[PDB]
Image (cartoon, rainbow over all chains, first blue to last red; front, top):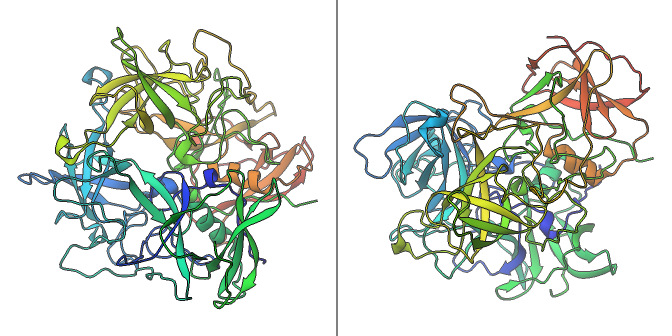
Length: 308
Length: 311
């Protein structure tokens, strides 16, 4: 089977690390960042890695049964997890955490829904705003449990519950750090089964990211909470479907404008599932709204890209 | 010609095209008094999107735009002046029922509005505003470019770029959730336009097969499920869009196969307009093996008699 990319414009792509559209392509040097996100990880021949699964609707979502955590002034309840599919989760599963688990340090914000309540109970009484913080000693998804900090109304214990992600938050002592992995089993345990860290090795090259702005419900005034993924969800899903054998270490890809039939820039798509471009410095790319990446040809790691 | 194909995905690898949550089960039932005319998850087998259908799950029942104050109103205290959910500017003269992804059911949609970021010291989730978007409000006019926001938790700022992220539905004392009743997209101002057509299983012994999810319900339906049923999962819509394989007949025969046994569990008709029928009578939730999936078999005569779906 020949390798292909889906034909999708920038506005037709979903971030693989949070359920929101891709807004731009962005390149920057790694500097002191370890680029080792666990969602949106997939090889060109269709092998999913890290905590990656197929559904955008499962990314940073959680499902399970609540249990009371009385006396704890942050996490008043815990969530006993399953997979987002509803299937049973066990810590012995060869994954860093249940598939779709957040892969950034900090506070994830969203809404927990539980047992339905009568109409007369009031407006959105089965909707509880919650913070899921990785700096909490209760953030241990690998061992099947996470802490829920309710903002207003009490979360009920012993109810089948779904967490729907909305954005991130930054409070006075919990910075949002997109390139720092959570301790999936808590601070006393090492992470397991990780998709590897990625970096450019060819001189003059940098990683290219698919960038989104994630809503931020507390903090980052006059700033944007960026979440940067290595592959859009659509690319992950396409490689998984196709499972086309990789013919070389690198797929040469070009961003084309079908309205003009011209190539705007080119990039190297590595077999392990990330992109490099020829550029030095932090830079937001100008892409035409109707443009798209296309597979050009198989090359090796030594291919010298036209400066972008 | 280019062969028609389905993506190879199990029941737990499918997304509802009418609400951004996974498909939970396959479900068949007679239409009865329901008019099946949903506007999200509508696509022909040869890849023509219809109604309010677009490609992103993150856009389904999502809204974007700018808030305006709506004074003197205890229900909609603010309005949202809409763009497309992509952020592209919206023109009411666009040949759409409403901006792509607009809710396609009557009742209350609940979610969170997020706006300009606030300082850390402002407090917890202060830039997260719980809102009801009701279709029975006279302010529900997405075709015209504006919808009403009913605040429940936290104050909505007027005059700010805003995103609405859907969480679930709600039913209050006088607003039932009716998944098969289309909203008035232009409220009281104009008749609905540009609609994807209604669907009915006219064939003897056949019923629609739905991709079913339970939508979270934040008010009402105690001891009941808020179901949202779609005609195609989002991944099928997107596949047909990508492939654009020419339809060779009115009906494609499809089979639900277990790869582990090789056996066909049941067969179904996948109609060129983008919906499925099965040979069964009565409301029935299907039990499929976790590893099973639909596959395209062949183009068949329009009068092809399906092997009974069975239980």
